[PDB]
Image (cartoon, rainbow, N blue to C red; front, side):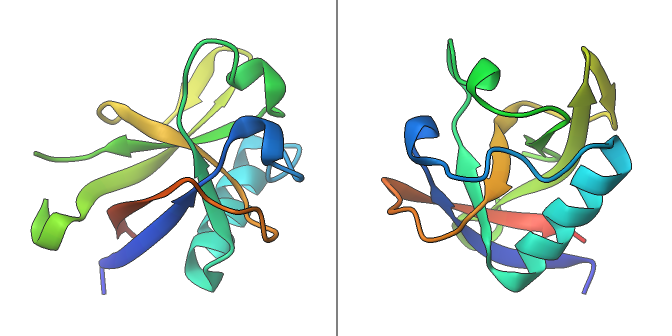
Length: 113
């Protein structure tokens, strides 16, 4: 399937134990997709002071369309030193590894895969 329904646990930035997916744009996009598939991917909602507490390169989910079954359609954009790889809509948040942190909420997305 071109799209996959996921429910991403929303984590508080200060709870996150593994603060990025790796060391290159290609690696973080690779690792993000693997974690999304394995159900081991969290989402941190981006506000003032959040991104400096996470490791670059960043992986964002961004809205790719205006929402089947409650699931917002999204795609992955990486960012490294202010340059983004990919072009998409509004940021829903930044993806991080999920290693058992308790979420505050869930974000239903339809991921273009």
